[PDB]
Image (tube, rainbow, N blue to C red):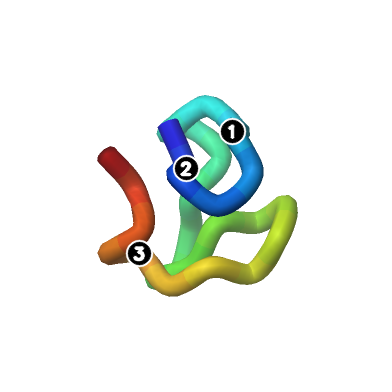
Amino acid sequence: YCSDCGADASQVRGGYCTNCGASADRIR
């Protein structure tokens, strides 16, 4: 999941969370 917004990890592309724009390293 994204620690910044809670989106599921499957929503990350191109190095960012596609919902809130967090950098990839915010995924846990």
Does label 3 or label 2 sit earlier along the sequence? Answer: 2
In the rendered structure, the answer to whether residue 15 lies left or right of residue 19 reads left
- Is 23 placed left or right of 22 in the picture? left
Question: 2 above or below 22?
Answer: above
Image quadrant containing the C terminus: top left
Is 23 located above or below residue 8 in the figure?
A: below
Residue 7 in picture, x, y percent from top left: 60, 33
- Residue identified by numbered label 1: 6
Give the Cα distance between marks 3 and 1. 13 Å
Q: Nearer the viewer, mark 3 or mark 1?
A: 1
Dot 2 falls on a residue whose secondary structure is loop
- Which image quarter is the N terminus in? top left
Q: How many labels were placed on the picture?
A: 3
Residue on which disc 3 sits: 24
Q: CA distance from mark 1 to mark 2?
A: 5 Å
For disc 2, the marked residue is: 2
| Left or right: 15, with 8 as reference point | left
Circle number at residue 17? none
- Residue at 56 percent across and 39 percent down: it is 11
